[PDB]
Amino acid sequence: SPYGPEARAELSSRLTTLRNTLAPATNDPRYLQACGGEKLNRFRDIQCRRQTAVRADLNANYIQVGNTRTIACQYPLQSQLESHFRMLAENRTPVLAVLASSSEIANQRFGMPDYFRQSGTYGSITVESKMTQQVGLGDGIMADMYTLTIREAGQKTISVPVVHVGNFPDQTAVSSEVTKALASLVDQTAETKRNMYESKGSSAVADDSKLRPVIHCRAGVGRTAQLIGAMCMNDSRNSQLSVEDMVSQMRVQRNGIMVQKDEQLDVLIKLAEGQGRPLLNS
Image 1: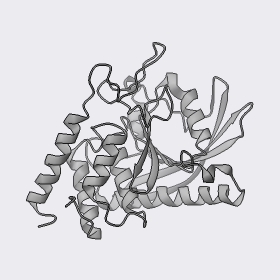
Image 2: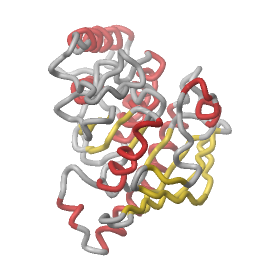
Image 3: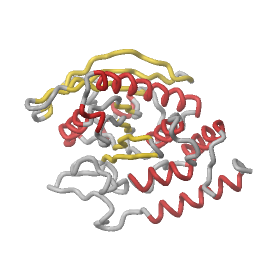
Image 4: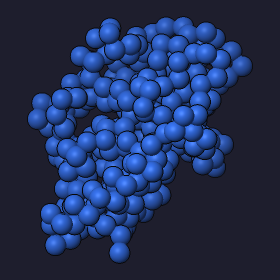
């Protein structure tokens, strides 16, 4: 009954209502609007909540699901790379999880710059990419890891661990088992990096806006939301946080499309069921 079809339908009903409420109006005061004439949103209908926006020129949001703090964003546009790197550096990013596949990135029609597997200079910022380990996630899904060293005059140099799911499907959802494996890897990688900063007495530890895992796929609403849901379920502080809570929180803090597909929600529901976590709020 708590995970039966009627509970699942009720969850869907509540979430659909929320999506409708959060649909952007023309020049919606709730959503970030482009300044300067440059394209801001990769997709016109996938907008960035203004009050939680990380930077004025990025489609990117601070999200807190229960106690779990992250940043969710779109795959940055070519024009946005300098700002994106500055975000990554200023956040002292403990892990960047990229859920867009190599196939997607390679499709030049999609405008997804290969910004983390190659080195480059973007305005004032110089970035060096290095290959690190590779970790299997199940079902032949592979996480390729990198470190990005971000250098800029006047700024401290920051190295960001990257977890790239190079063969993450976009046509089908990955299983709860793959999702769990990915959440554990991303969490573990963030933990190691955050520990390093703690050991150096970094001032970023005291700052709520910093040390956030950064997660993006192509749009930052499907695969991204599925991962963030799994990560929040991995957080021992989040007992009794329901699936309704986690999805509504993602939606209010980014846009109404978070967890876009029923296929993705099914994964979150299965993970919740495995923990005996509630789907709905009383």
